[PDB]
Image (tube, rainbow, N blue to C red):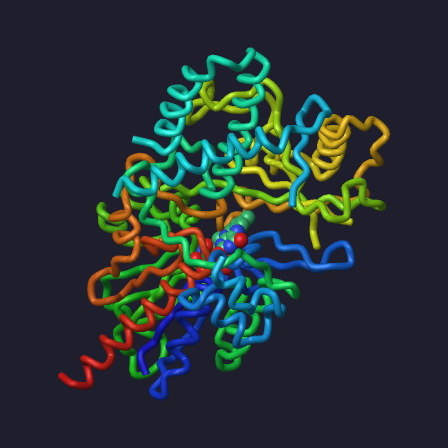
Length: 469
Ligand SMILES: Cc1cc2nc3c(=O)[nH]c(=O)nc-3n(C[C@H](O)[C@H](O)[C@H](O)COP(=O)(O)OP(=O)(O)OC[C@H]3O[C@@H](n4cnc5c(N)ncnc54)[C@H](O)[C@@H]3O)c2cc1C
């Protein structure tokens, strides 16, 4: 059969390999993975006696049209609530940096203002951030009754919603997120849920369905040589259009290479990763699209200091405002970008996106644990709060084979750029899959899976056309 090489063993590469290998007239296929394990940005680990997810956490929109929801149900990875029709159809403590609780009514008021504005942006099919700020500023000019203290509290609360949105988009700033394309991203119905035993159970299940020795780990690709006529070392010295050159020196001829490497990797290395250089159209989509950093900081405590019914500890930074912030501006300290902490169902998980998140990665584990212990002592107004016992944090920007968390349609790029990312090279010598190749489900596990299946289907159609001719 034809020789296929899949670069990367995340859910896109695994989905492509599974669909191709399950074909009754299967090709000779190898998956080349840079790291020691499969799953890529789905990365579940044994930590603090439990399971922590360093990458993907939720099935976003766990309903009928979500293929990740469908697989997780087929595989027995979901609990009873997650499987329910009620769930498919669809608890915080808010702390100010002054060590006082924030009014629930005020929080609701600002959430309605902020998310109503988000809903408006999703209908314009410059930046999301600029639109929100212009509308918020207009509303501020109508806050006649409020004393300067109330207006200050309202802007501070709004700043945390902007930081939460930075986590959602995987951007440093909403001012970097293109306005017109924003609404193309599709939200499927359902109350987002976890896979209790680990999201990695999903990719381990797909991986195990592949023929033995399909995936080679610790086998990073250095350069894909395409548009050539390359002899294989053995008889009958057949010519192949592609030669995959591995970092370890391996010379692998192939008829088709499915590239599923992250956009951050392509941004750093597209100039050396492809020989000849990618066509300009594709090179420019790689450059123009966004690829931001979002990290998780897990903190273990000997005893919980939060209420047992508490699921998220939201932080509001006093005297902060989104109206002062610009696309490339930084917060006063890296930790002011942190939105708060999800209580693991005694573990907390802090979320932080952007340049402050990349800066966090440069700090030692010790600095992060100590700094966040002081932040927690500050925001809960408790100087005797015991320090966290342990820390485990993701470092997505630093990861040489990822270089960030996920794609977004940045100012300067459109949904057409996600289509350019998916466009194959001539003769289907090189195909592209991955979350940054899906126009409406980019930045998700389901987008990545669907893109893998799309490339498997494109190849099967070519092979079927060779038989007919
Ligand atoms: C912090 C974080 C939170 C997220 N939260 C969610 C969430 O809750 N829900 C959700 O649906 N999505 C979420 N996502 C997004 C989701 O994880 C991804 O969109 C999806 O997993 C990407 O799959 P992929 O196959 O496209 O890429 P990857 O999973 O990154 O797979 C690409 C593979 O390519 C390999 N590789 C790279 N370079 C080379 C090379 N030169 N040679 C060989 N192999 C190479 C990598 O090691 C990797 O295994 C999150 C991601 C992160 C990081």
